[PDB]
Amino acid sequence: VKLQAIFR
Amino acid sequence: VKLQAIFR
Amino acid sequence: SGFRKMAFPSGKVEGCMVQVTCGTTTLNGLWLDDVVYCPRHVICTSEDMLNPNYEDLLIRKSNHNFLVQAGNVQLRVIGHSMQNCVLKLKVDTANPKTPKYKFVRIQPGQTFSVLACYNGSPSGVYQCAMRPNFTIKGSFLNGSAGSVGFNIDYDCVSFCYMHHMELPTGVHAGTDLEGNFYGPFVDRQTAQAAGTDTTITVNVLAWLYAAVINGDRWFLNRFTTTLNDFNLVAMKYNYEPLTQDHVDILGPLSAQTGIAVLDMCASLKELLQNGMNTILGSALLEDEFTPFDVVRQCSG
Amino acid sequence: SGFRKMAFPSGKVEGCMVQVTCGTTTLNGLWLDDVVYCPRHVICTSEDMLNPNYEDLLIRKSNHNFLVQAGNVQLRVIGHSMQNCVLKLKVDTANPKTPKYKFVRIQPGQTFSVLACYNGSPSGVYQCAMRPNFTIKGSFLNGSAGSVGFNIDYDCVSFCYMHHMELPTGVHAGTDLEGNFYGPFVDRQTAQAAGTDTTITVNVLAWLYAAVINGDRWFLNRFTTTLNDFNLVAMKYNYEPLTQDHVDILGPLSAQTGIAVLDMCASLKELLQNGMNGRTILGSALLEDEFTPFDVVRQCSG
């Protein structure tokens, strides 16, 4: 389960 | 063979 | 002639896609008038993803914390609010490329064009269908959150989907443009799984009509039957129940082909045990085409 | 994750689609800069198209006989010329929405996005592949001529196709943006038939690699074979002869999966002898050859 925003 | 423009 | 899975022209939607950044988290945003729409997990971090408190994380945020970049112009956010699973960022300048648009929530089986974007820039377009388990079989990578699904009727862009996350099986889940998810899904990194997928029935029937229209007739068989006979094969093969408002929608497709709606229903049963024994390049009954998609493409 | 038939954002092309009318015949035109490109059979009628002479029909027309309509603006034609099987109509107003563009001639197997238009208005977009028999399996109605095929690299829209006519078998044929047709086809309603179509090999192999990324690996095996012996079975099902340049472009996809190219050719071979046996690959029950190795990396990777 991945929230598909770019996390840095 | 059919030319695919609208002929009127 | 010819039948293909074709998507709506995304030109009017490409003019509304911006990039939304809160701290270091970034996704895509929908700029309509002076309001930007985007998923609410942009306010999260790599550690606030298991058990996120969106209402508390938003309280800790101010207007300057939201960085919206519309190409060369960075939009100044002068207002923010949360509605379900999306954010509303009120900017000072209305979008000049705003088309006529409404927000709708689609039913399972209905199709819509997905404009995949990354950092506010469109990447690709493809047609997708609301699966019965309330998921979509799309193609999304990291940074695709904020990508929207839409349908175009004349000049009206009916926004009906916004991407959020991906399930461990490869399918994706999102919300409407009001924040309400499609299904029992939440914007948390908790172990979530969608229900068992059934088959959209009104969609395979419309695809069956598109075959005899564009050429393929090698599979036609020879039976006529009634409505109850359709249920004698629907439940075992995980096929969605047919309604009576439906057969009115398959009406124009049945009259154009001379084969009544229920006349085509007789061909379904023999097709499910042994198969076809290619059909538009597919060896399976395709349920990703709605009767509206067939009429728009075949007889329009 | 996920693999889908993806088309390029047609926004930059929707700003160039106009409608060109000559008498009663009407099709779509491509408005780039101050020149409009469209098929040359718009100057024809319903009665002079079996054996049409095109070079006089242009000399029997003037600039005022061509009516170009960009939405509500009627563009004044200030010049006309013929280049191969397309018409070039110089208008007085340059298109303010003209993107960076080139004209390219693709090879069979390469893909491009088709923006289907009618009366100068775009209707839909879908990915198409140049079949080895120089046709495309598209979706076109009457009045779809002038619809263009394109590829977008960053902000450059490389135009490579323009629709013209439809074959009696259901497939379609067109020219590049210089008028040169794709194949042995001509823009006249004479008895024409497309040659026997082959299968793009690198496209199935790249499509197979896209399945390994998405979990599907039931078609993989331990067999390793040689290129010629794979070709000695490729030309048997006369899949297109695979070259060493072909094995080279499949390298980046082979390194990401660790599966050697020759090992996938053996996985392809056993697939043609036994079939699927009730199994699907990427949701399709057949080998899809409409996906370029570039299309897979663009979708599966960053």
Image (cartoon, coloured by chain):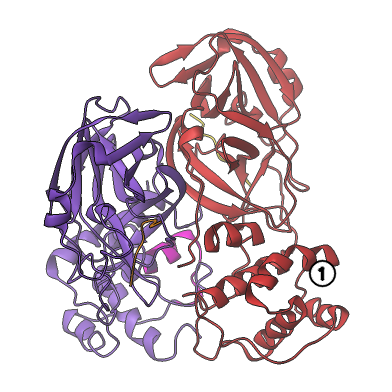
Chain colours: A orange, B yellow, C purple, D red
Whether residue D98 appears in magenta in the rendering, the answer is no
Quadrant in which residue C133 is drawn: bottom left
Quick one: B4 or D163, which is closer to the camera? D163
Q: Position of residue D119 (x, y in %)?
A: 44, 30
Q: How many labels does the image show?
A: 1
Q: Give the extent of the magenta segment.
A: C208-219
Q: Is residue C234 above or below residue B2?
A: below
Q: Is residue D37 above or below residue D297?
A: above
Q: Is residue C83 above or below residue C17?
A: below
Q: Residue shown at 67%/78% (left/top)?
A: D258
Tag 1 residue = D241
Judged from the image, the secondary structure of the residue bearing numbered disc 1 is loop
Task: Name the amino acid type tagged 1.
Answer: Pro
Q: Residues within 10 Å of mark 1 (few under 14, many from 20)?
A: some
D194 left or right, relative to C280: right
D243 left or right, relative to C146: right
Q: Is residue C246 above or below residue D215?
A: above
Q: Where is residue C67 in the image (x, y as percent from the top left)?
A: 31, 39
Quick one: D85 or D13, which is closer to the camera? D13
